[PDB]
Image 1 (cartoon, rainbow, N blue to C red):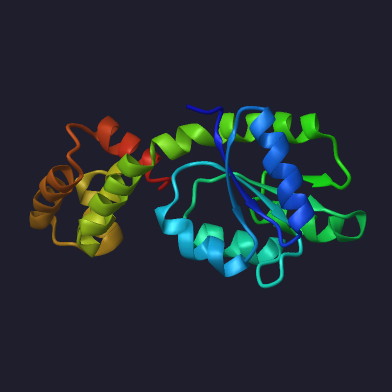
Image 2: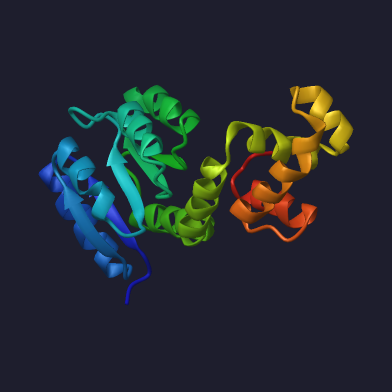
Length: 202
């Protein structure tokens, strides 16, 4: 039992030691990486936690780390540690999705407060991930016309307008609707909308 797990990425041994110590005092669990690839190799097997990474890790600077993390659709929040000269690189990382940055040297409590906020904001999506991936799988199981019919239903088109808009035979609209509802496991249009919510289709 811990206040959250932290994945530290820093090629500087003294930073790793200093983070290791201060995060433990605050009650977090910690796993450390000195090598860019090592983190990415482990990443499919890691449980939810907050990443705290040097902005200029050799082989995974802040930009590259963020590009890979979202390629993996990771829900982990990322904080970037940086010297003042690399603040602009940290800026790019936040535009790509990093939660916040810290200019070194920073105080122990500024990091741990930032981590607490990051974990609190990211945890809900981490918790809802297996179901959102199930929903995405359902959406991917639709045929192309079924996907169009789902879109037309949510957009509020009549069956006649769905047929006309997508060039589907009128006699197949209810066939596709039924397939949509079964594959999505939706019991109504509102339910279909909320599934499209959780799959971010709006």
